[PDB]
Image (cartoon, rainbow, N blue to C red):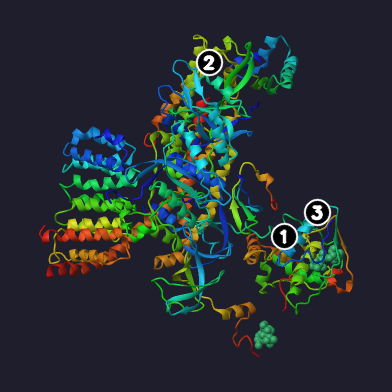
Amino acid sequence: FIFSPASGIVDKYIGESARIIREMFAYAKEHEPCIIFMDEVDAIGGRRFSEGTSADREIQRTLMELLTQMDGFDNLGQTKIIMATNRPDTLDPALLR
Amino acid sequence: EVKRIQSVPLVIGQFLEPIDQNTGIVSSTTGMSYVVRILSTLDRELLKPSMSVALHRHSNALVDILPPDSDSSISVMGENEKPDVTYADVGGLDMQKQEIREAVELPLVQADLYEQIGIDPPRGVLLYGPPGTGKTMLVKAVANSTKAAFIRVNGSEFVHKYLGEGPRMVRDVFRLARENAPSIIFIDEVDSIATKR
Amino acid sequence: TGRDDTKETVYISSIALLKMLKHGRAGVPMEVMGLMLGEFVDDYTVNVVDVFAMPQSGTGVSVEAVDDVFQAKMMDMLKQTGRDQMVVGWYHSHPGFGCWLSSVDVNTQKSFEQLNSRAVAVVVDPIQSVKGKVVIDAFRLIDTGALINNLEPRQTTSNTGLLNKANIQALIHGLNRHYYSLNIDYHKTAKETKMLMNLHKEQWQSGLKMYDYEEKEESNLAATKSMVKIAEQYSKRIEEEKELTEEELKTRYVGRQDPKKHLSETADETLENNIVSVLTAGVNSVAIK
Amino acid sequence: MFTYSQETQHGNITRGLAVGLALINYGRQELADDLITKMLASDESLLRYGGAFTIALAYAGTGNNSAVKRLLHVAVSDSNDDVRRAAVIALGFVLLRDYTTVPRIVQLLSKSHNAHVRCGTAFALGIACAGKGLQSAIDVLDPLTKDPVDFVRQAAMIALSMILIQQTEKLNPQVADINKNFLSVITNKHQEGLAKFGACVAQGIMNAGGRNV
Amino acid sequence: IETVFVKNIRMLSFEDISKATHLPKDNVEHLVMRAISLGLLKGSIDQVNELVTISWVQPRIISGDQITKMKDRLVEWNDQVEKLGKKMEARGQSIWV
Amino acid sequence: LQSIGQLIGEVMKELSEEKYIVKASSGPRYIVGVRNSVDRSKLKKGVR
Amino acid sequence: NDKVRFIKDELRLLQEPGSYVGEVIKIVSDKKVLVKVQPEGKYIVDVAKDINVKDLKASQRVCLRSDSYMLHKVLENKADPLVSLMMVEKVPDSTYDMVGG
Amino acid sequence: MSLQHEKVTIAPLVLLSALDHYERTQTKENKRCVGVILGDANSSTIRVTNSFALPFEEDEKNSDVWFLDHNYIENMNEMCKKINAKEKLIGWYHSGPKLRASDLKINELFKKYTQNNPLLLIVDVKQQGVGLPTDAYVAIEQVKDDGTSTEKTFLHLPCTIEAEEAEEIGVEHLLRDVRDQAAGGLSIRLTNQLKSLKGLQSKLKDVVEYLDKVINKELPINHTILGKLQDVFNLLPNLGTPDDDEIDVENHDRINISNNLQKALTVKTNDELMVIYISNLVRSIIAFDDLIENKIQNKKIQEQ
Ligand SMILES: Nc1ncnc2c1ncn2[C@@H]1O[C@H](COP(=O)(O)OP(=O)(O)OP(=O)(O)O)[C@@H](O)[C@H]1O
Ligand SMILES: Nc1ncnc2c1ncn2[C@@H]1O[C@H](COP(=O)(O)OP(=O)(O)O)[C@@H](O)[C@H]1O
Ligand SMILES: [Mg+2]
């Protein structure tokens, strides 16, 4: 197990917050079977946005990284996602997929 | 004597453009731009357009060159990997199937078919739609079927992580594609990379 | 005045140069230090015979990082075997900077000068000796009071007038205008020249050592193939190139990046190899059996 | 003197005695032949440095092919710069008698780009072709005056002022131009001291003696 | 093992072996095969040329008589290189640089 | 105290036989040598 | 000899301290040039004897010899900002035989 | 203890050093020098990093009488431990010239300090031979087939040299020589080939006269020495086999690329032949116009 809180994988440095989550799927393929519990995700749950602040394209960079992992030429595995959220209609519908 | 300066260790810059046949502009990947002498009796045919290159460590000078094949962002993901979905996961999606076999498959089998009729070839393919529609699925289906070279990059493989990292990663993927041409470059999502605003 | 009053030409022994280098290289990146032992003859010839290192410190080079105990004891070891002389100066390493004394060392050189006024400081770069050329330079202080008395031309009397420099601006100002440089030459006997020149006991017996012939076939195959492609290149070049202005024509029709020169070179290279390979095989087959 | 060069350990003495050996064996030729063979074969630089000038002074004014043949060998084949020089300079002493052919011997040696060899090509010609000028000699020296390296410049300016000793521009204009080139350097402070030394000494060589020598 | 070692030839007709060991041809073939199993000789057999070509001999104790035989073999190759060396001195005279 | 540090890379790409492209964790790519301690076949892409 | 003394002289020439690409922001008439180094920041720095401030101008790339940043040559390049916009958008030009009708 | 001294790689520093110590104690007239070797062990390659002199006075009445300071050795070791702490006692050097059997007794004394088996490194100060001036040996204990009990005897170790990156480039800075054992250009390899061959000739001749000396002059018979010569004869090449027919065939292929390459250079050089002749034609035109111009140049010199 890990784990990842919604907001301790978020970093100030960009391409550093992509780094953890890419490398945390890597870990999952050596230490397999694995369960990846995302806890109380609403942080990068956010939609396309980016008519707001710069925060919302920080969300966007980190979200795109998850999709190539989940389904891509990167394939899984014996790695499992358990995603815990407190309201699911916050989410981007590409995380309802 | 002149072989010892061609030898290890070396730092890798990137050559921008010449100003001369024995003086060039290179950008080091240390985030410093240098105007540097170039060694005579190297070949310059691949040098003058941008390409990876070896620069000496302490002095900083263009002392040897590298081939464009090596110093790739990520290698071919199409001879050292093989697609994992065929056209047996396809049944339906035939509307897109008439347009994809024109677009991807026809310049690989022979580019010259276009040329001799006197239609100039279409460019790039954008696939759009909810990602649940099997866009991604179709790319893997025709790739297993054509069995040409394929590249698996993503924007989290072009992403900035130190200074001047991110433009270098862009230049390298096309350089590789042309060397073993023809080739299909796949970037799975450009959602982050490009934003309307 | 009444002497030559010029900085010694440091003649560093065959032993010594290697020993400072090995001792500096192990400690990279941290600064290294140590004593040069030598003898003083002439007024301007110091031959440095041997070296010893003064142990590491956690603050690196300091005047403080001199320890009388290590220096004197190590000295009494060499005394018993009678290979000791007198301290003619000292070495230390800047691998993070070029040749020039740092702000700390000039003050260390002032103490050392006090003890013996012929004391040199030799700055060794073990990290720019990864080249074919070793970067090493020697300096000795000229006193602040000395500059005032304008005694700088005194030090450059009776020399070839050939000095060394290291970069520009800051580095160069320290070099010429506060300290004095003198070239470094390398001293050796004919006994030592023979000891270095030798190699193994089958290096003088390595032309009988033929290679595996798979590898020699490889050499045959590559050279013929590659020359087809540079020859193609050679055909394109001489189709034009015969109007006026030589450089222009060479820029136009690929006369720079010269294939004419390059085709000859490959051919000659593969040609000298294959004469010896034939020679080797013909000797070994007949000689042994 | 031969023995004592080994014993000493002061750099001035090792050189001095190499020169002094050459001096005492002036005019000796075949007499001094054992000493030449020994001094050239020594692996130290200083005994070879006198070693060359023992041929020069021993075979002074002789037209012996063998005397000249030895000096050419030393020049190219010895891997020490200091050694090369002493051999080029020497040639002029031997060929004092016939100074006509000397610019052809050294044409080669001036082509090459070693500082020490070029510095000595300049001198060889200076010693040899003194008296009244030689048109081929003047011509060779002209790249060597305009040289990048300061030491090659120093030697070269001196060497021309021997050749064209006390000659006027009312006889030969090329002498005015050569002199005027010396005056520019004496003016110029943005060169090294080395060029300046040679400029002063060489300009006084021309006008020496109160304009009479 | 004795016959091959002492001889400068290393191929023997079975006839010679048959006469020595007082065996038929059926038993020379076994004997040779056994030597190979135990590892006292190694080689290969042509029963079509009728030779046994041995290619390796086990080193063993070397007695007074054998040293003389070993020695002579060495004189021949010593002289052979010396003769051969004069020609190679002679040829390519111009260059020895 | 007498032991010095080492700087991590990864094998980015085989250049020749004895020259390797590493991407150091300094960030800029270097070209490096081999000891006889390693083998060609113990090195492969994505090994630190 | 031309050959071997070209190799021996290129070993000297290749050895640098690093020599950069700068761009001139603006001149100052104390005889100095405000140069923004392309990675780094701005430094007002003196010029060589082959160039002066009237051979230099805004948005013209200079070479610097970097141990003090002392201006060497004008570079053989010049940036223009209007083409940046125009290219990045990307549009050709036409004639009236490509509109006709 | 162990044998793990299969290869001994020896720094060039050490050799240089050994000659330097030898002269500064001024041991001549068959006097010897012993110093400690410091370096690595528990490696198959034994690395000789460094050496330092021990005061040792060796007698002239006997070879069995010597003075050596045990108290000295530790002081030397602890100071050098401060410099670099990968240095431990790995033997002691003898200054040669040759092996002795009084060195066996000295070996056993150095065996106390060591946690490896002592290296006796005969560093020759006489520079004899064109090959290495080092033979290496380690004292090892054996029984033997003769009827010989508990023997202490020294088995030769092959000697190699390695140097570090910093150390090697130190050599290259010092020296500039091209060597007589180098395998460089065509000429140089031609010289090596003759030299290598004559090398072998010299060693084989010794063996022949050594065999004589067993069997008439009563030198000892030893199964290691005989055993080695047997191997030579068993793995000896043979010609006239199908191996040889193939070697000739390989030989034609190498003759073949030399022939093709010889013809190729003829074409590049004949290109150059023509072009010198084209330049002459153009320089002719230039020379004729020149003469009119030289007339005015001759004239000006007469007029002024
Ligand atoms: N036509 C179809 N036949 C079979 N299975 C399908 C079909 N379309 C899609 N699927 C399956 O649905 C999944 C999603 O498809 P795909 O892998 O192409 O990604 P995508 O929609 O581009 O996602 P994103 O780009 O956000 O990662 C795959 O497992 C794919 O095999
Ligand atoms: N007058 C014309 N002559 C020829 N081709 C034309 C003409 N007008 C339109 N086209 C073609 O149609 C394309 C679409 O017209 P375009 O110039 O992009 O349109 P807009 O009017 O939207 O600015 C052109 O690129 C060209 O191929
Ligand atoms: Mg997809």
Give the CA separation, mark 1 to mark 2: 68 Å
Q: Amino acid at mark 2?
A: Lys
How far is mark 3 from mark 2, CA to CA? Answer: 68 Å
In the picture provided, is H198 more to the left or to the right than E19? left
Distance from the alpha carbon under mark 3 to that under mark 1: 29 Å
Looking at the image, is mark 3 or mark 1 nearer the viewer? Answer: 3
Is disc 2 on the same chain as disc 3? no
Find residue C46 and name its label. none
The answer to which image quadrant residue H283 occupies is: bottom left
Q: Is residue C235 visible?
A: yes
Left or right: where B9 falls relative to H189: right
Name the chain letter of the residue that bears numbered label 1: B
Tell me what residue is drawn at x 66 percent, y 15 percent.
Answer: E1
Looking at the image, residue E41 sits to the left or right of residue H205; the answer is right
Badge 3 marks a residue whose secondary structure is loop
Residue at mark 3: chain: A
Seen in the picture, residue C238 relative to C158 is either above or below; the reply is: below
Q: Quadrant of residue C100?
A: bottom left
Q: Which mark is residue A29?
A: 3
Name the amino acid, label 3. Answer: Lys
Q: Is mark 2 within 8 Å of ligand 1?
A: no
- Give the crowd class for mark 1: few <14, some 14-19, many >=20 residues within 10 Å: some
Residue B148 got which mark? 1
Q: Can you give x and y, in whole percent of width and height, for residue H59 in the image?
A: 46, 19
Return the residue at label 2. Answer: E71
Q: Secondary structure at mark 1?
A: loop
Image vertical order of residue B133 relative to residue H261, above or below: below
Query: Is disc 3 in contact with disc 2, using a CB cutoff of under 8 Å?
Result: no
Q: Position of residue A96 (x, y in %)?
A: 87, 69
Q: Quadrant of ligand 1?
A: bottom right
